Image (cartoon, one colour):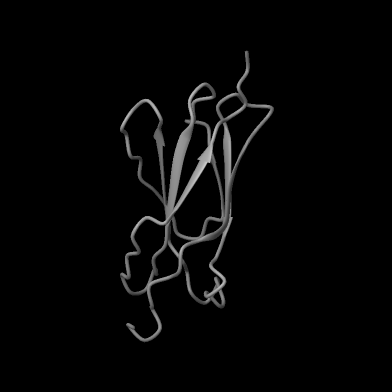
Length: 109
């Protein structure tokens, strides 16, 4: 493609785990795609967006080099659809929203 800055494949190992010590924290962890070689030499910008299952509010978080995002803005009583995208810091090769992780922080009741 763009010879080098090829559109990064959908992030892998994308698992949103709920913190039992926080009824609103969602440890959204992930990793670079299997197709992606070195995540260091190629700063992969991850675009995370968490929208409540009761409100159509698509958030916008940029992770220049984040692989473990912790969001305390997640509702424990409602599911959160956190979609993760990929892109290259060098050349703008925006990748459409792929992985749509489903999670729910510690439902303290």
